[PDB]
Amino acid sequence: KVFGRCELAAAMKRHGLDNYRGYSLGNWVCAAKFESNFNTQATNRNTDGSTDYGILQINSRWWCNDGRTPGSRNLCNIPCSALLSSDITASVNCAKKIVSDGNGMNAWVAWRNRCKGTDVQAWIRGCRL
Image (cartoon, rainbow, N blue to C red):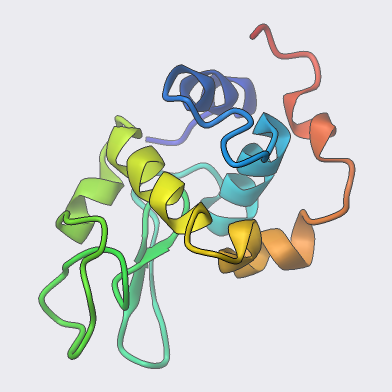
């Protein structure tokens, strides 16, 4: 599924991500924009053999099982394919665990490099929420 910007904002709010761990909804929308361009089916292979999955590009090295990432963990206790669904629930629940792991949203390199410290409210501007 390719979400619209306000559509994704609304779904993220519906699943409790707005202001989760102190990160406003604009931060989460911005992260999704630059991680996946709002496409739930986005997958990207990393140099080390792991893969990033879904709207928030969650990595099989730690967070989900894809059966092809040797010596990795599955800390969200889900198949990585669950992070590709049109319903964002599994990606949101896993992202809640990731952003609680110690480094906040810095876990998302595109957030740090493209969203952090910018006017992230622009991502929700005009949305009926």
